[PDB]
Each structure stands twice: as C-alpha cells, then as structure tokens.
Length: 117
Image (cartoon, one colour):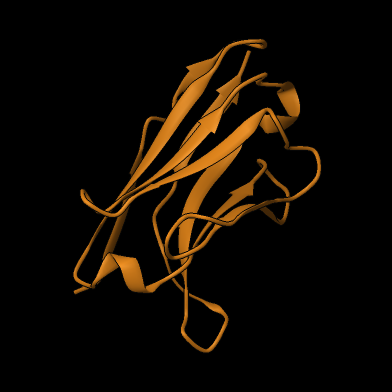
C-alpha cells in the first residue's frame, strides 16, 4: 500500500530553477530517510541527494551543491528537490527512494522526466 509519487518535472532551459515534489502515503513518513536518485537517458543510476528523518542532515553527491537543496515536509508527507543552476548534465529521470530500515532503497517512485534545453 506504500506509494511514492513524484511531480514537478518537465522541460526547462539552462540557468533556470525547478522544484520537485514527492508525495508519500501508506506508511508513517517521519520514520524513514529519503533519497533523490536520477538516471540520465541511456545511462546508469546516479545518487543525487539524501535527507534524514528530522531533516536536520542533508547529504549531497558532487556535481550538485548549492545548486541543489533538498527539503522535507513531515506535516504534509512530501519530499522536495530544489534545483537551481540547471545544466544539460542534469537532464534525467528523477526518482525519490525511501531507505529500508535495514539500509537499501526498498521502495521507489515512477520518477519524473527533467530535460534541459
């Protein structure tokens, strides 16, 4: 019954900003850490961001910092990926994935397509 739906994706142009949202349901939200993982067209999976339970700790991979900032609304059960300084390398399918309590990314979303002109 666990559902992770993402939105906000679309066709943007270099130098603009975007905001991606991930509505979550079917499970208590404040008991899991969250991830943003992206996949460039025809390429492999790449980890982007990670936010903790309380949202106090945010870890970003390289190629993204200052540009990307991750947020978490526990009151409305939604995840956020604020994407500034968008580049042609950023064009990818963005999934939000929740961490299994034992570590791995147990449940994923169907992702949103972001393309950069």
